[PDB]
Every structure is written in structure tokens, then in C-alpha cells.
Image 1 (cartoon, helix red, strand yellow):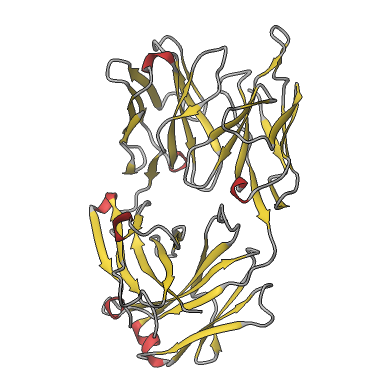
Image 2 (image 1 turned 30 degrees about the vertical axis):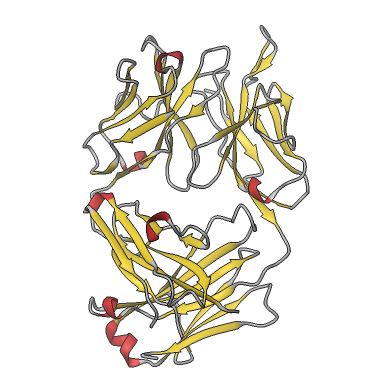
Length: 216
Length: 219
């Protein structure tokens, strides 16, 4: 089973956006397709639903007249057209799937697509080392400062280092830009013997930065 | 349209102990026709989509461990976790399918209670690279501690700071059931270069007395 999510990112109020999940490995026309959204920090909201053959279409009141759900069973694709977007529509949009009336319980396929509705301009993150000093445990990290919108992804040594890592939730500063740190604890003895690099990616500003982090 | 209301809004239960979450529907979701409750329970771990735990109010999904059970009928339902494990930390949602839109509960944050663990404290001076931009960010890290409550004091030459720092906290770990916290002190290059001693003082329940980490500007 393989899924490809696309659309999403920054869009200004009133403008429009087209989300899609596409999938292979399940019988695409055996299922009613749904969109669920989650405004960041808040809870799940049923948005839209569509029968296997596009026969019946249902929208939640919050989106009726603005959003259009559709599907192409030939292209194994589920679409959501977001028009007349407003700040409150900012959310992670998830693709969901139910067999029939006899079992209408959601299966979620695909990890969610972040839509940020804002007038604010994109700005790439400044990536700065958090250098380790001089029981035998040392912390080091990356400061990913002054970016917009969400999100950024941070890995270490291109995914080779996952053990010990804490990538802090973004916090909005008074400037109207996000900032976070990603840190990792490692043995002291390893500090000189091993290489440590943050892989910061920020799709909205087209910023890929690999920052080396070394003592001092 | 039917309205789901969970209770409590959040819940903190010790390892190996019962956790009970309640869901209530504005109308009944029992279908008299087939005598089935159109009511599911979902788990949502941080930065993942929801996983189905329990359907028809009391039928457990395959893969879902024994300790998860559903109960109730009509308008009052109960998700129960009989012997809570570290990995059960998540937000639990009830969802009704008697109508469509198939509306959700507001959600219930479940936290794991464990023996107090003291934070490892580390301090980080601003990078030479950052200073060239004209602001300075000093970062204090409290690593792998329980419970979530901690006091972080910023001291610039023994002067206690206020309104110039921001905290971020990790989602609770699914293995050791601890948190980590980052305090970020933000000042201008000017103010950073005036003063010499930068110190972060941590008060936490797992420490007999406040721990302080500090540096002098330029080693």
C-alpha cells in the first residue's frame, strides 16, 4: 500500500488550493472517501464525504458552498478543492476511507496535509548550532529560528541518528515568525570521533540546510 | 446534528492502573433495527493520524491489546484501559456514525503518571554566526524529567530576567514517560555583549535543590 499526498502549504485568505491523496495497493472503488481536518493543537472535525461512485456527497456546515470533494477511481485519487479560504480553515487535512453502511468506521490513509491560511510572507529558517561545551553525557543541537509558515522537518546525519533526539514544537515569537530547537544527547567520548549534522528542510521557502555542529 | 462530549478533557493515571474515559451523545446512537451502537473509539499519538481501537461501542479491533475495552449503549459510552502502559499516552476520541456528518468528541489527553525523574540541564551560548545578524539566543535544555511542571530562571550577571524568554515542551515519551523542555532567552547583540555571566537555574520536584548551569561570554 503506497500513498502520495500533495497540495497544501501557505495560501492567503480568499485564494484557493487543491489537496489530493492518490494510492495503490487497495481497491480504490471499494470505499467511501472522507476528509477530516485538525486545526493545530485542537481536535478532529468531519469535513466532507463521498460514496464509491460519487453518487452521494455530504459537507459539514462550516465548509458547505466553499469546498468541493471529488474522486477519480481510474487515477486512484481523492481531491478536495478549498475555495474562499479563511484563517479558521488552517488545519492538517487527513484522507479517510470507509467500506460501506455495514461498517462505516474510518481507516486513515496518508499522514495529513498542512494548509496555513495567512496574509504573512514566507520566510526561510536561520539554522544556528547549539554547540556542546568542554555523567559523561553531552547535549548538542540546531536552533531553527525566524521562519514562516509551518512546517520544518529536522533529521540528524540524514536519518542515521534518531536515538536521543528531541525536536521541540514550534513556538510563535512576537515577531510573527516560528522558532524551535532540535537537540540530541550523545556520549562525551563520541564528540570528537563522530560527525553531527542537522538536516533542516522548509518546503515553503525552498530552504534545504545541512548545518555541521561541533564543539566550542 | 448529534453532539459528542467526552469527560474528562484530560486524565493522568499511574503505570499498571485503570484509566476510564466517558463519551455522551446528544441523541441515542443505538439502531433498534439491528441493535448495534454506531460508536467508535480512536487513538491519536502525536504527529500521526488516528487509529481505530473499538467499534460498535464494545468490539475491539485486531492488533489492539487486551487491556483496551469499550462499553455502554444508547447515549453513554466508556473506553477503559485496564493496566495502563507507557505507550498508551495519546489523545482518545469517540466518534458517532448514526448520522453523517459522523461527528467527533472534543478529545481526551491521557498522560502517564510515573515516579519523579530530575532533568539533566544543559546551557548553550549564542553561535558566532547568529551574533553577525544582530540578536542573541541563549538556550537552556531540561532533558527527560517527570512531572511536566518546572521553573526556569534566567540570570544575566545575577540579575533575574522576565518577559524576554519562551518555553517549548515535548509530547510525553512513549517509552520512559518523561518530558523535555527548552527555555530560549532572546536579547540584542548590544545587551548580550554588555554582560559576562549567563546562567539558567532549574527548580523541579525531582531535585533536592535548584540546579544552575552557566557560561562566561567567550569561554
